[PDB]
Length: 86
Ligand SMILES: CC(C)C[C@H](N[C@@H](C(=O)NCc1ccccc1)c1c(C(=O)NO)[nH]c2cc(Cl)ccc12)C(=O)NO
Ligand SMILES: CC(C)C[C@H](N[C@H](C(=O)NCc1ccccc1)c1c(C(=O)NO)[nH]c2cc(Cl)ccc12)C(=O)NO
Image (tube, rainbow, N blue to C red; front, side, top):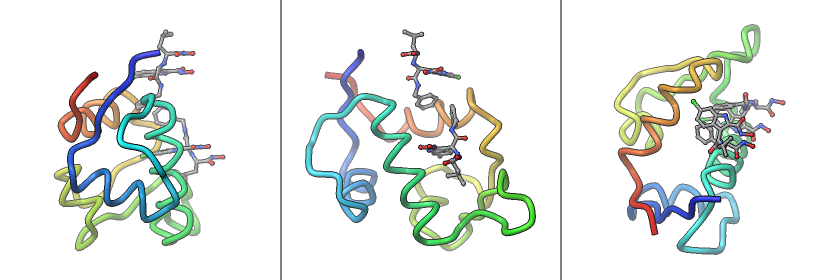
């Protein structure tokens, strides 16, 4: 699998949910992002596919006020703008 190196702000976010490393697979990045979204309760309680991220680090990184977990290609792109491959 492709190994990626999150930029400093994304890495800070990942490590806040127990990520240990400086290089990751995209699946690991998505896993830790999910953990962040879950533990901070950023998902809509009625519509769990909706993530709210205005005035959160996640929003500043992704460049959106909210997104749907179903927007896979977009999420991949939003994550990728915070990476570099290694
Ligand atoms: C509220 C949400 C975090 C719940 C979580 N959903 C995730 C999920 O939909 N993953 C499929 C997927 C596939 C490709 C791109 C984005 C998302 C998911 C996960 C995940 O690790 N699910 O286990 N991580 C995510 C990160 C982002 Cl930014 C968006 C979605 C996910 C879940 O546990 N469903 O049982
Ligand atoms: C070899 C090839 C099939 C790649 C595929 N992995 C993709 C992947 O990196 N998934 C994690 C992920 C997916 C979407 C955003 C961020 C992170 C991936 C998957 C996938 O189904 N992984 O199991 N789905 C993707 C959707 C988009 Cl838009 C972009 C990437 C993926 C894989 O390893 N599948 O077992």
